[PDB]
Length: 43
Length: 48
Image (cartoon, rainbow over all chains, first blue to last red; front, side, top):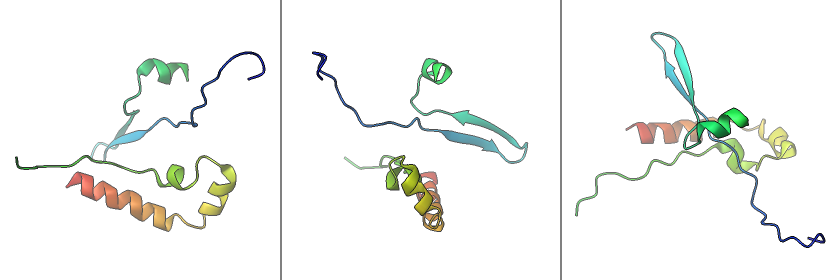
């Protein structure tokens, strides 16, 4: 950059999401595969 | 050595085809019958 800094440029990423579903009781939950919980809370 | 399994890779059809571009996703809604078959086909293979 022109401000004297070298910047790494990575591609834009997306957090994975999965649904845990129990049909008999009609219950569900969310699974963010390989994502730390702190990142989910902050973003 | 006897192999017993392989990695289970699942693919997001919407993110793979359109890289998060809203203009591409608008065209892809005409599809989706094909994305729904790819998502379910890989689900069955990983389930078995």
